[PDB]
Length: 210
Length: 56
Image 1: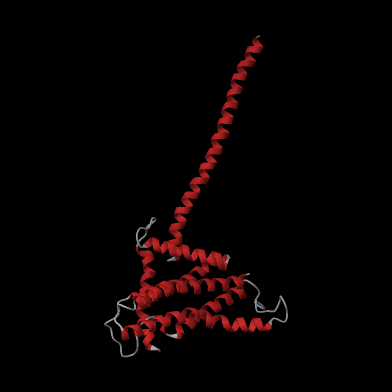
Image 2: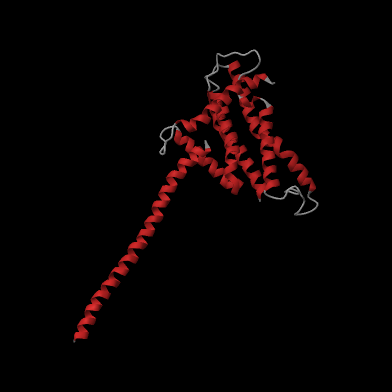
């Protein structure tokens, strides 16, 4: 396996598996500090899903919330985790998203997701790729089918991996006193692009469902 | 997790909505009941008017 990413992705997935039990740990009808964030993020899933997917947003609530909150916790492990002293001879210790493979996995997941919706809910024989509006629109089918997953992934992946490198490229020259607005802009936009992959996934499901 | 969060949300929403709709229904109940109250009152006092006019 590609170890340099997998080793740290294991402990980030451990953070995920613990947040899986955070649900069943504390029941609060009125959630005070911290859990109100959980309810607000559930509301955020409601927002993006009901806004873009359409009707069967709720069985896709899991599939959108997973990538959204996972980009959240991976931004956490990338920047906000104190990792100055730790040293690995296998490679840099930045984030789970350091490898292309995680983002192409999210890509294929979203792709087969809207393909699944468009094959089940619509007909099996033909879906939006079939050339109904104008029968000479096969280049549109080819291009969009070929470009959606990989660049869908690249949109997030580029910024996240770029900052994951830029942080150590900055510390290699100047200590942490200078790179901190860079950390700020990164922690700013890394959750936005999480939202972006989420809403574009949702829009592709809506395309499949229409 | 989605089950748990949507579950507590559904708890509070369900109880508030049921509250409001039963409130509307019991308001309908009081209007109808007091209408029939004063109607039966008119009926009894009208039986009084009837017995008065009849003995008259």
